[PDB]
Length: 118
Image (cartoon, rainbow, N blue to C red; front, side):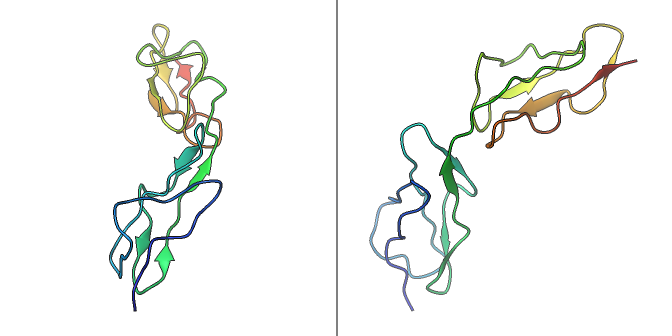
């Protein structure tokens, strides 16, 4: 059994640095310019059957907002499949949820934006 270079994927490509991978190998599937690679940073050919293929989609974001508990670390008008934003509770309040989130793939802010409560 062998594992030749992997096939294409969700509008994404595949190019590690070889043609045969046999087994226990992996391949970082490339994605179209402007597409986020969701999944493991590398496919996994184990047993002549590539498995666990990531996706090359779009991971823009809405905005890591929150109840008087915005963030003040790495925020931006737009994000992608990461861009972690630390939430800074306004004042005298506890961030109910997560004081540190990241724009994951799919357009959002995981974990659920924190909530500056009292």
